[PDB]
Amino acid sequence: GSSGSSGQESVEDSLATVKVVLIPVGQEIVIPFKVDTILKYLKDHFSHLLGIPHSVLQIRYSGKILKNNETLVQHGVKPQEIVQVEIFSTNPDLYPVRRIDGLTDVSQIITVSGPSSG
Image 1 (cartoon, rainbow, N blue to C red):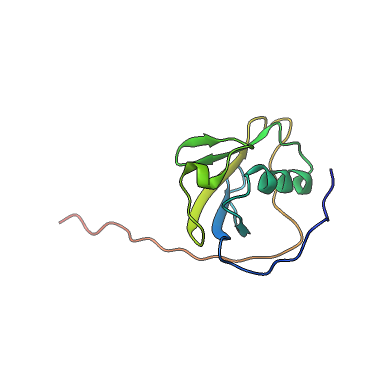
Image 2: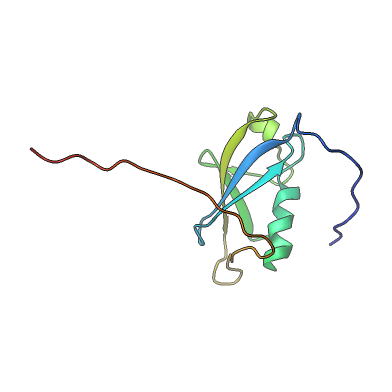
């Protein structure tokens, strides 16, 4: 499609932190997204980049299936907040999900294991 046109605005009053995790890949990607802007906008992006259509690619949140015309504020998301969403494709055999190219981000994590038996 078309990607370029963009006005002027440099603020973070509404923009919230939306973490993205690849289901098939398992990688982690963080990118700022508007709470008033539909999800599609964010989706269509990964689609083109990956080279696969959105007709097969979908999103998941709170064990629910978010729609394109759907919005974060519609599900219950406030501005300047942090969340976590997962991405995956219904038809992996036809349109599999690959890693993004262009930038190199990094993340961290930690977990506690179980103690001894006795």
